[PDB]
Image (tube, rainbow, N blue to C red; front, side, top):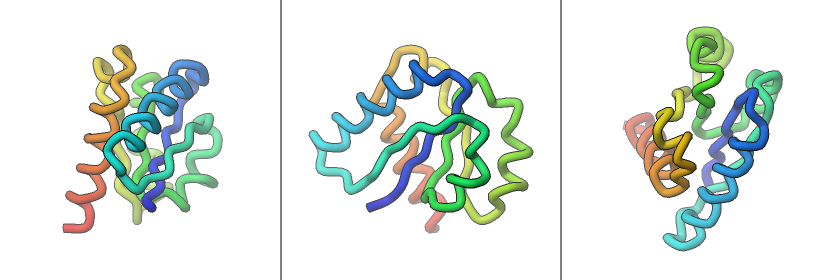
Amino acid sequence: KKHIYLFSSAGMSTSLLVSKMRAQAEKYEVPVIIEAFPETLAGEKGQNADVVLLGPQIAYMLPEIQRLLPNKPVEVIDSLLYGKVDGLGVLKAAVAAIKKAAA
């Protein structure tokens, strides 16, 4: 089971996106664990993630988080997918980042 961790300053919308992603992962039997955390834990919690996703509110922090976790794929969630709360779409982007990372 791969760990997908989302980091954002917007607690509610991120947690709502996480609940929809979990529903989708269950529907299609994707072996993943999805958790949302505040941006302050990106360095502490990120070390255990298989893929690190940043909420669009903290996109400007991408370079810093990449330097903090040089051995993890880190990327920003598409703002439209995020605003629309597209659990399936974001789940797809996360699995993709993992695949593109393992090869």
